[PDB]
Length: 214
Image 1 (cartoon, rainbow, N blue to C red):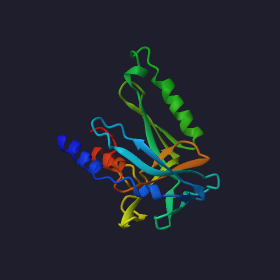
Image 2: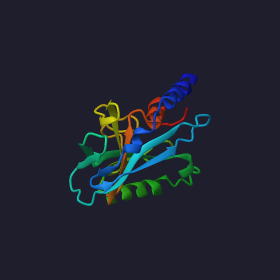
Image 3: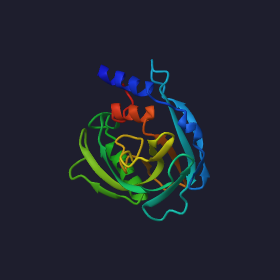
Image 4: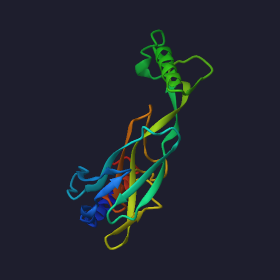
């Protein structure tokens, strides 16, 4: 869609990265650092993100409610409750690469491996009734996954003044409370970023629905 490329260019063209130069301070007491990262969008050289970043401890976490206290100059202080864990549902489907022929099929092996990893994660494994052969879904796993990266968003309230964006909970599409990076296993730290709502990364995420293509 050629309108997408133009809409992205316009968003980049209008992005002023200089207010973030005033961003200093802490996230959960960890001093932030501001980074400039090229989005490497061809033909759009100004497509450069500018965000604050802090790697913060989560070794106190026992619950699902991770609290993130943002104390950055020119940003109104706010405390975000972020979901520390969520349920991931996956399935194992018997594919051609795992099933060279009907007589030499390895799908049962990889189903058993899927089951064992599910169980070792504390998940619920359910075997699908019927034989596990080509192009069938053979099992599901419902397991808990844990936050790795939290990209918060602030918006301009007045000139050179920012506040927590109550609409964009995350800079990652689809920008909601659970649109963060979750992975199996309990981490020791979480990487927290702070983006302006005008950041080209968010424009890119929005126009490509998180795919970052076009």
